[PDB]
Image: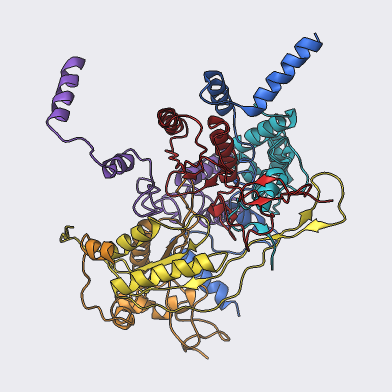
Amino acid sequence: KKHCEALKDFCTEWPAALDSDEKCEKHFPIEIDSTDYVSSGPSVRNPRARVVVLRVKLSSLNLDDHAKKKLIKLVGERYCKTTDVLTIKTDRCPLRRQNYDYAVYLLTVLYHESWNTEEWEKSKTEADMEEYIWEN
Amino acid sequence: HYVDWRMWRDVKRRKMAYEYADERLRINSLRKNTILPKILQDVADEEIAALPRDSCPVRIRNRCVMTSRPRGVKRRWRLSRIVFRHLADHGQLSGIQRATW
Amino acid sequence: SEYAFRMSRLSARLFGEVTRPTNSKSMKVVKLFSELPLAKKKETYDWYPNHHTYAELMQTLRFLGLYRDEHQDFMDEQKRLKKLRGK
Amino acid sequence: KNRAARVRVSKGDKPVTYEEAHAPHYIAHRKGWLSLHTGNLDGEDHAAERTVEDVFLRKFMWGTFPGCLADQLVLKRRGNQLEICAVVLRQLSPHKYYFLVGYSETLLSYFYKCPVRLHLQTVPSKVVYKYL
Amino acid sequence: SLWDVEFAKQLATVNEQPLQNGFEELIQWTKEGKLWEFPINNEAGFDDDGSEFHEHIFLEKHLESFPKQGPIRHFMELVTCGLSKNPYLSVKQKVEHIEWFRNYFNEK
Amino acid sequence: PVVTISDEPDILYKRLSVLVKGHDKAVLDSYEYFAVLAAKELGISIKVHEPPRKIERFTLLQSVHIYKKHRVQYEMRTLYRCLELEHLTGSTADVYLEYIQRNLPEGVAMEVTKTQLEQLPE
């Protein structure tokens, strides 16, 4: 208790963000995971605990509304049944800051290459419809 | 400063195998492939065969660490259970002990 | 239909890369290039510690006196016994 | 007849120490843990190297202290170090003890680049626990 | 000019207070990179001097014209995709792999 | 004892998932009590559960050389002690981790904290 009361400083207080993580999700639902284990001995490095995702909401950022009929199915294991957890995971690189930079660049390139549609964006098919688009 | 010569044998094998790995993986991937006729496949086979002996992970025999004793050795701990069993009996291993259940 | 494959091809073409499919046995190349080999794993090459310069330092310490090697003391005793009874 | 760590009885006059007077299966009942490291988890790496370092440092401290050990050592790990709790036997003079401790500390620091600071517990008589 | 630096250090030490406690020894140990970090951030380095993801997933500059309908271009694209799908390999390693593969496919 | 508060942007942990692994129960109980005391002194709630162990037994021969009749039973245990926190500044989390690691039990009582940052957008 004495050590805690002493070290109460050497920190930065946080604003009334309101617990429960409700307002955090309402505002910035971005949530990139990251962990770190512990080891005993001379070595301290532990690159194993580098698991990191790329969970960034598309509708929340608000920069490529046209991707509603694209990213809803172009990405892998998504399109949940009940809840909604949009995450453009792309763990093809280890670091986190470079991960976010690559995410920003990918969003920019997606905006660019999607505002000029490719081919089968609207003319889907006749037996696979995640969102109704003619014909049928 | 190793006990038996098998230790130096395995050390040299591991070293010469870890020396090169990029070309090994590239040629292994090029091998199993339906694309491109067997011409380039056989060319890459001859290329990978041109490498010298020893330099190959196939020759690596996972033995112990005391004097090369491949008898129930644990690769996670490398060294055999000669001293590891002594520690597990005494209690110098944080957890690894006799299964009390 | 192949709408899943079409969407995958579109996502790939969004930046310029593979688009058309391939054979079934051709996935070995991707499986090998997407992971590291076994020779580079710590559970193979990192097997026998050096103990060369370390053993030399231990022998120098033994010859220094401040640190002793009980096993080497017994070895020297046996060597003296042999020199007295050998040879 | 298995005879791991348990000592075979012969006569009720065996001055055995405390740690030495314990079977090798009481690690979860009576006997504690001497050395500790994350290598013995389910599952963390760094196990073989830690065990080798422990087994080496044990013999090192036992050789540097010939006969001045009341019982086995009790290794530890706190940071980039390896605390060694020992029950030293009052044999040499305190000046020699301090000199040897400092020399060993400096040597280990300059050798393994890891200040393995140890700890002593001077006791004249051995801690006899049973007369096996 | 060694004696000058020696005298300067001696004067600076005489004009300052010694350790006088073990906390100074701990601070010196931390400065000399002996003990771990406070706390074990598990991130000492590994930044790779900023890779800028300009060689992992984006195949824009890495193109080299070749008949798309051909099998060689498809194999190269598949190999590049498999390489990009490997977050374990380094950047220079992947660059060397791609360069060697392209040179071998162009020559042979 | 100085705040040393600057004006640079800091990171805010969103739901700090924490988990402590440990073999025996006494050391784990001591560690969890210390962690709960530290959290209460900081001002954060927690929640625990009762998970089982992890039977990763590995059997081998009894004698070091010949003989294979009877084997030996060797295995390690681990009990997960979840103590996830919620909402805490980067500096506060760093100081908490420093205070927890300055006396972490070596080997036994292995911590498994999982952070979840946010990283501001463009």
Query: What is the letter of the orange chain?
Result: A
Residue C35 in view in this figure: yes
Residue B50 in the image: above or below residue E1: below
Q: Which of B4 and A115 lies nearest the eye of the viewer?
A: B4
Query: What is the letter of the cyan chain?
Result: B
Give the x, y percent position of residue C76. Answer: 68, 19
Query: What is the letter of the purple chain?
Result: E
Residue B34 in the image: above or below residue C13: above
Q: Quadrant of residue A33?
A: bottom left
Query: What is the letter of the blue chain?
Result: C
Give the x, y percent position of residue A92. Answer: 47, 58
As drawn, is D14 to the left or to the right of E69? right
Q: Quadrant of residue C48?
A: top right
As drawn, is A15 to the left or to the right of A35? left
Give the x, y percent position of residue F88. Answer: 30, 70
In the current view of this chain or complex, which residue is farthest to the left?
Answer: E15
Q: Which of F86 and E21 lies nearest the eye of the viewer?
A: E21
Q: What residue is shown at x 20% (from left), y 35% (from top)? A: E18
Give the x, y percent position of residue A11. Answer: 23, 62
Number of callouts in the render?
0
Question: Chain D rendered in what hue?
Answer: red
As drawn, is A27 to the left or to the right of B62? left
Residue B58 in the image: above or below residue D94: below
Residue A53 in view in this figure: no
In the current view of this chain or complex, which residue is farthest to the bottom?
Answer: A136
Q: What residue is shown at x 71% (from left), y 51% (from top)? A: B32
As drawn, is D49 to the left or to the right of C72? left
Structure colour scheme: by chain
Query: What is the letter of the yellow chain?
Result: F
Q: Quadrant of residue A104?
A: bottom left
